[PDB]
């Protein structure tokens, strides 16, 4: 639900409205005209009107473009701005004001040695009591910076009145005599050029316990990214983070119950930039080949995530996400301390079964080598499907409770083999090695809670169910002994076991009586009595014999095993 909602919005490239710096050989420039700088300052002044955050689509709480936010605190809804300083002027003689036009006898000159002017106090931007009610926020993308600037003779600027001019005049008034952005001294001079130099900025984010979804911004300029780093501090909520195609340093402080979800769609697909928007292409090959887990460091092909805090835990899972189509998505459940990950699928039974070859081909193209793939899904009507899929031989078991009836199917590739329309058993557990699957359960003989049989079986074909083992409790064992006693010499062969299974009505387990059970050459049956137990096993010729029996009275211990020829030793 988180990933599908995140993956829809066509997000802008960071710096689109504020302007991306273009690296002219020296000192990558930001703007090179008078009206361009006035427009940049208009964009800055928009933050007075909209506040520090703007609501896009009423869904994404996106910061003002190119604003230096250094800290966010969701616990008290307060932020801290960074520093945006600009070189101050000095000197100049004959200061005069005429129609808010500054006249001089000599133009002031720009000095890099005076402590520069900070802009943000001039703006009075709100930094407390913010409405952070949305779960979705795109992270800030601008580092702290000092703006060098240059003046040149620019005619025609006397009549320019936009909000950027008012912000510039405010900067002038707050620092009288230090900043003159346009002035007449025998000529009309104006701000001509802006060149920003960035400082390393660590954006500290303090989380709360509610659900939060973050989006990483796409910054195309290497300097800006390398001067940017994120540091989260969790507190025990559900947090998701959509990774960007261009890597940024991220550090996370783990608390006890953090559940973190890292969407990595932009890492596994060809990414293109069209009209300031991001377009995802085909799956890029081998994107996940470099998946590195260390107890404190998770590395994907170029994205590194460092973890801090409660790193010692070994009971905590972390999810990664990626979509293959509109319905079938692929998850990765990771345990850091165990360096473990096992793939999962989700979304459609019939679609997945029909296209299993293609899905497995894609998973191989991503470069993941885990042998078996779980399957978990919840549909719109809340019927839950779970199963195991073999990546090698495409044998897959799928279980789900339809209505009240448990349905259990086995597939070999893309065609059915078995379909139990009513599996009447409790404590069902399903295991698998590549080809051999095992279903263990407990069956109550004729709804009598006293007489239970623990069975372990294996599905072979449409009417073939191979029995691996049985365990009969006290009353079940007394019934077994009576059955031995009443058969007049047919107790040394497997067909005896088949007749017994027909006796207790084992076929009711599947609801239909056209089932052929296969008693293998290792079938072992354990019967418990009031004092001890006895285990019978089938030999190579398919004859049943006591393998091991033990029981103790108040003063005596009786044992028997096939090693000594079933001599009952009484001590």
Image (spheres, rainbow, N blue to C red):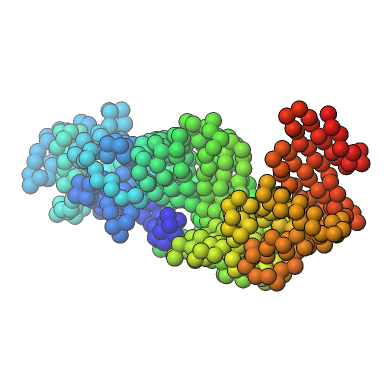
Q: On screen, 100 above or below 513? A: above
Q: On screen, 415 above or below 267? A: below
In depth, the one of 51 and 391 nearer the eye is 391
Q: Is residue 377 visible?
A: yes
- Where is residue 427 shown, x and y percent of the image? 59, 51
Residue 361: image quadrant is: bottom right
Q: Is residue 363 left or right of residue 208?
A: right
Residue found 50% across the figure and 46% down from its top: 247
- Position of the C terminus, as image quadrant, is top right
- Position of the N terminus, as image quadrant, is bottom left
Residue found 51% across the figure and 53% down from its top: 321
In depth, the one of 483 and 411 nearer the eye is 483
Residue found 45% across the figure and 38% down from its top: 257
Q: Is residue 196 visible?
A: no
Q: Residue furthest left?
A: 98
- Where is residue 493 shown, x and y percent of the image? 86, 58
Residue 416: image quadrant is: bottom right
Q: Is residue 331 left or right of residue 6?
A: right
Total number of numbered labels? 0
- Where is residue 343 shown, x and y percent of the image? 60, 52
- Where is residue 76 shown, x and y percent of the image? 27, 36
Residue found 84% across the figure and 56% down from its top: 491
């Amino acid at each position: 639900g988180v990933g599908s909602e995140l993956a829809i919005f066509l997000l802008p490239i960071a710096g689109i409205s504020a302007g991306i710096p273009s690296l002219v050989n020296n000192e990558l420039i930001l703007h090179d005209k008078a009206t361009s700088v006035v427009n940049y300052f208009t964009h800055l002044s928009e933050s007075k009107k909209y506040g520090p955050f703007k609501l896009e689509d009423d869904k994404i709480l996106s910061p003002i473009d190119d604003l230096v936010i250094s800290e966010i605190d969701f616990n008290t809804d307060s932020i801290k701005l960074g520093t945006c300083d600009i070189l101050s002027m000095e000197g100049g003689s004959g200061y005069t004001v005429t129609n808010d036009i500054d006249h001089f006898f000599s133009s002031p000159y720009i000095n890099s040695n005076i402590p520069p002017l900070s802009i943000y106090p001039v703006m009075n931007i709100q930094t407390t009591n913010l409405d952070f009610s949305k779960d979705l926020m795109m992270l800030p993308n601008a580092p702290s910076r000092l703006l060098w600037w240059e003046t040149g003779a620019v005619p025609g600027l006397r009549s320019l009145e936009t909000d950027g001019t008012r912000l510039l005049d405010s900067i002038r008034d707050f620092y009288p005599g230090k900043f003159y952005w346009r002035f007449y001294a025998w000529f009309d001079f104006a701000i001509t050029t802006l060149k920003p130099v960035y400082e390393n900025t660590n954006i500290k984010i303090k989380l709360d316990k509610n659900t939060r979804n973050f989006i990483m911004p796409t910054i195309t300029t290497d300097v800006i990214r390398n001067n940017l780093s994120y540091s989260f501090t969790g507190s025990g909520g559900t947090y998701s983070l959509l990774l960007s195609s261009h890597p940024i340093s991220t550090n996370i402080n783990l608390s006890k119950d953090d559940l973190w979800i890292f969407n990595i769609d932009n890492k596994v697909r060809e990414i293109s930039i069209q009209n300031g928007t991001i377009k995802k292409g085909n799956l890029v090959r081998n994107a996940l080949s470099n998946l590195d887990i260390n107890k404190n460091k998770l590395t994907i092909d170029n994205q590194i995530i460092n973890f801090s805090g409660d790193v010692d835990n070994k009971y905590r899972y972390i999810f990664l996400n990626c979509s293959l189509d509109d319905e079938i998505s692929l998850m990765i459940e990771i345990n850091l301390f165990a360096k473990s990950y096992n793939l999962i699928l989700s979304g459609n039974k019939d679609y997945l079964i029909s296209n299993l070859s293609t899905i497995i081909n894609k998973i191989n193209n991503l470069g993941l080598n885990s042998k078996n793939i779980s399957y978990n899904y919840t549909d719109e009507f809340n019927n839950k499907y779970f199963g195991v899929i073999s990546k090698t031989n495409q044998k897959s078991i799928i279980c789900y409770k339809k209505g009240s009836k448990n349905i259990l199917e086995l597939y070999n590739g893309n065609m059915l083999l078995f379909d139990s329309k009513d599996f009447i058993a409790d404590d069902i557990n399903i295991f698998m090695k590549d080809d051999i699957n095992t279903i263990t359960g407990k069956y109550y003989i004729d709804n009598n809670l006293d007489i239970s049989v623990d069975f372990s079986i294996s599905l072979i074909s449409k009417n073939k169910v191979k029995v691996n083992g049985l365990y009969l409790n006290e009353y079940g064992y007394a019934s077994f002994l009576e059955f031995i006693k009443n058969s007049d010499g047919h107790h040394n062969t497997s067909n005896f076991i088949n007749l017994f299974l027909d006796n207790i009505g084992f076929w009711k387990l599947f609801g239909f009586n056209n089932i052929e059970f296969v008693i293998d050459k290792y079938f072992a049956i354990t019967g418990k009595t009031d004092m001890g137990y006895i285990e019978f096993i089938c030999d190579n010729n398919k004859n049943i014999d006591i393998y091991f029996g033990e029981w103790k009275t108040s003063s005596t211990k009786n044992t028997i095993f096939s090693g000594n020829g079933r001599n009952l030793i009484v001590e």
